[PDB]
Image 1 (cartoon, each protein chain N blue to C red):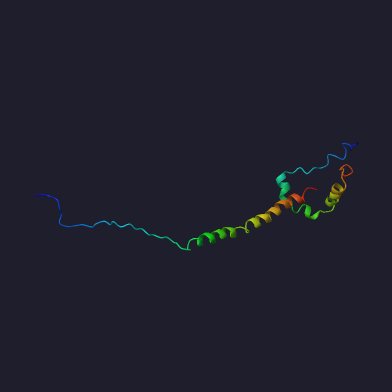
Image 2: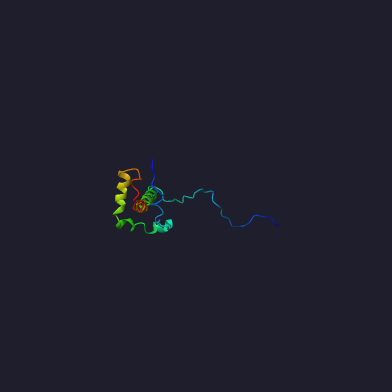
Length: 54
Length: 67
């Protein structure tokens, strides 16, 4: 099979601690709502997270 | 002439046998038992249901993140 390159990696990972990540944790997803549910259809409905990387 | 038997001063002590210090008998008991027992159940549903409210709150933070 095939795998995408070392490019489209090394993007800005949120380097925070787990407690400060669970600190807000409630106002975070409650107002963004545009890429996440689309990303869920990109993962739940369609499998193979290799067409699903963007 | 110096013998014993005194002129007076006697009791006696009893040969009696009694100490009926009762004691809250006769349907007064089983009454403090049942009401305090349901009082403990009355203390429930204000804590378990309250912790159940926090239990959905705990699972809320898991579902909000993880996309």
